[PDB]
Amino acid sequence: KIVAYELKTGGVLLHPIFGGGKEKDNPASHLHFSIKHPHTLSWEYYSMFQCKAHLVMRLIENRISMEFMLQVFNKLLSLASTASSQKFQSHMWSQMLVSTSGFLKSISNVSGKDIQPLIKQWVDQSGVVKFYGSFAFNRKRNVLELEIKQDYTSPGTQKYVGPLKVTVQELDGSFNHTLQIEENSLKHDIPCHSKSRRNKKKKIPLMNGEEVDMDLSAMDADSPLLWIRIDPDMSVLRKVEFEQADFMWQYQLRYERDVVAQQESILALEKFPTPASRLALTDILEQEQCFYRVRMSACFCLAKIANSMVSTWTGPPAMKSLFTRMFCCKSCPNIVKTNNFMSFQSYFLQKTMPVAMALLRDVHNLCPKEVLTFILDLIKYNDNRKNKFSDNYYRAEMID
Amino acid sequence: XXXXXXXXXXXXXXXXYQVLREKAASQRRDVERALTRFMAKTGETQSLFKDD
Image (cartoon, rainbow over all chains, first blue to last red; front, side, top):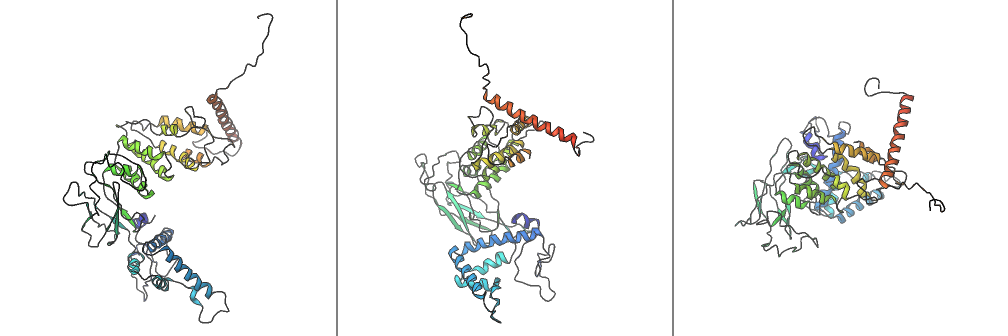
């Protein structure tokens, strides 16, 4: 919501500052007034105001303990509930106006850190920051060792945020984290992995706990890297653009411990590729206990990539096999029908998948005829009151 | 046995599973479209094309 809106429009700024004395001081007057007034704004603006409100409190997590947040808020409500419910202390009562300045003061009283830079970055420069953190590859048996460059410039609505850090996963190793700077024409290193060699023998030297995975399938002559990340806990308002080997994206989709990483590799592999191995790893991702909505956007991945399968119809008419191999009512002799609820993974998944199946088109007349008749058959085979769950939205998305 | 002894006739197994639920669901579709046609020509009607 936030990135889309402040690239549609200008910033969503959190003033302390007036234009007092008939002054404007409003670059964010890309449409309208904001400074002293509620009733100028748009619901797009007011909504994104609340959204930036969420995420700037996440930045205050990112500089300050949650326990300290409990401390701050308890001090707030202690002073307020103390200042309430009395005989009206005359001249001594407005402590329930607990606005920005003294609140900030109370924060720094709990822990005085450099959060006024946090303010003047995010509270007082309403800018979203893209990132051209450009992947380079040192220790590609390189003398220079595990290096990647930092880059950014994109005006219209830009902002330059420097000193932060970087989160990288090795093959089976350290979450490497690396500092950042301003003056952003930068080149930086990685706190290097070991010589991950003889990796047929180094099968799993402890990827992340007792996770179990083996592929030499990537460009694994000299690839001791697995995944790039900047701030997986989503600190900076970001829109990160970079490039890896596609193997690394797909293998991240084999597993990663972030839904963030999973759906962003979902988007990155929604752009370009079509190997059938992509389809394979997609379907593999769809059939486990991983996540619900991951699988919904994975369905839409299959939609795009099988739409790229016009001359490259290598795989089947896709995803019929997914209703085959994942759905046994009474072993389901060729058609899945009945009572497929109480397991709400499957609820969302059946709710979603035939839409992406109805997307599957290859250019002769885009011809989803099998899918057409199949979906009509899905609409046939709906349940009685054996499902206790009002077979409603399932109808709705089959209709969609 | 063709004259003396006798037997018993049950004569209706009809237990073809997928065919059974095909029968039931097809019949449900029938009753759908039937009541649709009924209140279609019954009540206030507006169309998709002109005069359907």
